[PDB]
Amino acid sequence: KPVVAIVGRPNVGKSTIFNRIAERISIVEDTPDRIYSSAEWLNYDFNLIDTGQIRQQAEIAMDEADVIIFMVNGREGVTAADEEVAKILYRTKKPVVLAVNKLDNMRANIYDFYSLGFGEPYPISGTHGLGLGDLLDAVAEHFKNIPETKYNEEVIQFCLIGRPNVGKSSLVNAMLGEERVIVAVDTSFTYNQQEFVIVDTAGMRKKGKVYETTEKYSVLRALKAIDRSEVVAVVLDGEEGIIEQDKRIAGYAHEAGKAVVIVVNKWDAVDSTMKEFEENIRDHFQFLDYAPILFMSALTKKRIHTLMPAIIKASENHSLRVQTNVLNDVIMDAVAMNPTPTHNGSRLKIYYATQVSVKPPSFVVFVNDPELMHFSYERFLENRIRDAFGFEGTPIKIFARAR
Ligand SMILES: Nc1nc2c(ncn2[C@@H]2O[C@H](COP(=O)(O)OP(=O)(O)O)[C@@H](O)[C@H]2O)c(=O)[nH]1
């Protein structure tokens, strides 16, 4: 069932590798010309795809395929022509893997290929079919995060999670009632003529034809939605306040690496009370600090509009992709301020940094010794980055590898 797309500028072995992991399909059940299932022998199954200036491939590809293999040529390196393909493929929420043709994993030791910014290279000799098992290992994993429900990439998916009676049902409509908004297990609406989807909106429709089973099945119901949403809205109870489950479902988002927002509903029904309740939230949600605290009301529409904007802001950042050149200026700037730690002689060195993921954005820092980068410096960098391009709404992770 999964769908994989080899992409890259022409004359890089795209056509070679395809035959490696190729029989064709014709008049059999499908959601599509020129589709193939995986080379039957192979460990796993999925569909391959022929995509038919390369902008046409790149879009048609990321229209119809949930894991994309972008393939350069390492005979003579990261071509000018290549960097524009990457630039096209930066506009996708789907995974991407980096095939580097004709190399020894040795000839692979090139920071240039990391720059392109889709993570680690995976070298592949093509004629001998070396280094390929690792590639399909790096691809297949993503099959485990492909949702069985799919939308156009320009659709934006989100959810209103929390404990019961807090506002979830009331508050969804108040938004839909606004004139900017224009009205299937989910609600598929538009705002400013742009598609939107509140994921599992039967979190409302089910609970009122059905006596409330128990905490377990509803939370699970919610965490399953979170797996499909890009922005979560953790929507509290303004009278009642903090607890277990709010935190529990809200902690899963950060641990899923999800764009979070903190809505405080039933604020009409509240009599300094903000900033004491804010730092009360920031105490008990001291990981969610990037995410903004909204003090709206569903019942009286108070600040109801302070919402879809904040989502778009969070959704925009969750995707937001930084230039490798600027980023390193920021990082070189980091150390000149605060020198790296001493481990009595052995000091940490930061050679080179680069973006690799999004949803949520993720950076690798290349160093002399990974464990020498203690978490303290790791966050210092994180805090520096956020004072540069904001990223206010989203989590970001910072891995680190030996050069
Ligand atoms: N009087 C009163 N009304 C409540 C109480 N709890 C909930 N409600 C009402 O029921 C609604 C519950 O909100 P809802 O959006 O359904 O939250 P959800 O059930 O978690 O989606 C509120 O807007 C309140 O008017 C309560 O303790 N007292």
Image: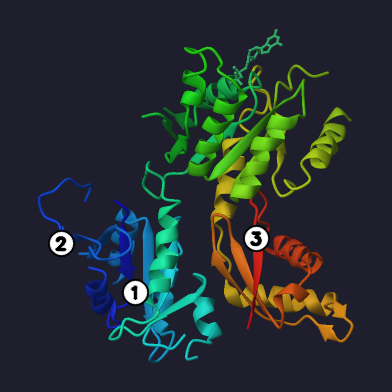
Which residue matches tag 3? 397
* 239 displayed left or right of 126: right
Asked if labels 1 and 3 touch by Cβ distance under 8 angstroms, the answer is: no
Q: Earlier in the sequence, mark 3 or mark 1?
A: 1
Residue shown at 67%/28% (left/top)?
A: 303
Which of these two is toward me, 224 or 310? Answer: 224
Residue 152 drawn at (x, y percent): 36, 47
- The amino acid pointed to by label 3 is Lys
Give the image quarter of residue 14: bottom left
Q: Earlier in the sequence, mark 3 or mark 2?
A: 2
Residue shown at 63%/51% (left/top)?
A: 394
In the image, the residue with mark 2 has its CB under 8 Å from the nearest atom of ligand 1: no
Secondary structure category for the residue under label 2? loop
Q: What is the C-alpha distance between the residues marked 2 and 1?
A: 22 Å
- Against 227, residue 295 (above or below) is above
Q: What is the C-alpha distance between the residues marked 3 and 2?
A: 40 Å
Res. 8 mark: 1
* 284 displayed left or right of 195: right
Which residue matches tag 2? 24
From the viewer's perspective, is the residue at label 2 or at label 1 nearer? 2
From the viewer's perspective, is the residue at label 3 or at label 1 nearer? 3
Q: What is the C-alpha distance between the residues marked 3 and 1?
A: 27 Å
